């Protein structure tokens, strides 16, 4: 268990680029971490994204969020060629990054209070 509730992380899911997140407890499972059906560790995260999104993410697809400029180092893990991404996706990623930068300046307690999602039945 490398991450705790309120920790800022980058998550790599589906076809999306490394995305700013906050580790949180799953509302149903009441844990922020678990071992999956394949025996691998996963963390529950909330994305700093337009549609309120949460996901169980494989530990290998999660990295500590040290700052927005860390993005180049994440790409370097795969390693002049650059991959494009839609402008609309970049715009939503920039808003999420802006939220993550504000969250990074807070204490873990402040961040949990400010950003944890409200779940409705
Ligand atoms: O909701 C928005 O306007 C928004 C739009 C694009 C990217 C990120 C966000 C915000 C995410 C937040 C998570 C927890 C508290 S705010």
Image (cartoon, helix red, strand yellow):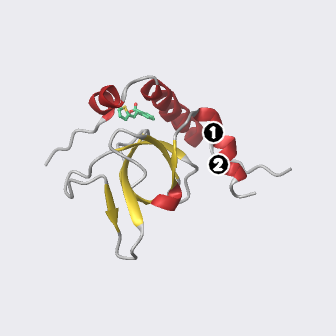
Residue 121 percent across, percent down from the top left: 13, 49
Secondary structure beneath disc 2? helix
Q: Nearer the viewer, residue 34 or 28?
A: 34
Badge 1 crowding class, 10 Å Cα cut-off, few under 14, some 14 to 19, many 20 or more, is few
**Mark 1 beta carbon near ligand 1 (under 8 Å):** no
Residue under the image location 26 percent in, 52 percent down: 26
Label 2 crowding class (10 Å Cα cut-off): few <14, some 14-19, many 20+? some
Instruction: From the viewer's perspective, tell me whether residue 78 is left or right of residue 58.
Output: right
The residue singled out by tag 1 in the image is 70
Q: State if disc 2 and disc 1 touch (CB < 8 Å).
A: yes
Secondary element type, mark 1: helix
Residue in the picture at 35% in, 31% down: 108
| Quadrant of the rendered image containing residue 106 | top left
Q: Residue at x 68, y 45 (%)?
A: 73
Residue displayed at 32% across by 25% down: 110
Q: Quadrant of the N terminus?
A: bottom left
Q: Position of residue 50 (x, y in %)?
A: 42, 38
Q: Is residue 12 left or right of residue 116?
A: right
- Give the residue at the far right of this rendering: 80
Residue at which label 2 appears: 74
* Vertical placement of residue 106 versus 115, above or below: above
- Nearest the viewer among 116 and 85 is 116
- Which residue of the protein is positioned furthest toward the left in this rendering? 121
Q: Which mark is residue 16?
A: none
Which percent across, then down, holds residue 30? Answer: 20, 53
Quadrant position of ligand 1: top left
Horizontal and vertical percent for residue 102? 46, 24
User: In the image as oriented, which residue stretches furthest toward the bottom?
Assistant: 38
**56, above or below 71, in the image:** below
Q: CA distance from mark 1 to mark 2?
A: 7 Å
Question: Quarter-wise, where is residue 38 in the image?
Answer: bottom left
Count the numbered circles shown: 2
């Amino acid at each position: 268990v490398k991450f705790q509730v309120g920790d800022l992380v980058w998550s790599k899911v589906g076809t999306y680029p490394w995305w700013p997140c906050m580790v949180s407890s799953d509302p149903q499972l009441e844990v922020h971490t678990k071992i999956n059906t394949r025996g691998a560790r996963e963390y529950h995260v909330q994305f700093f994204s337009n549609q309120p999104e949460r996901a169980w993410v494989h530990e290998k697809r999660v990295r500590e969020y040290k700052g927005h400029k860390q993005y180049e180092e994440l790409l370097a893990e795969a390693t002049k060629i650059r991959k494009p991404r839609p402008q609309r996706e970049r715009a939503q990623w920039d808003i999420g990054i802006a939220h993550a930068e504000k969250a990074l300046k807070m204490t873990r307690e402040e961040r949990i209070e400010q950003y944890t999602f409200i779940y409705i039945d």
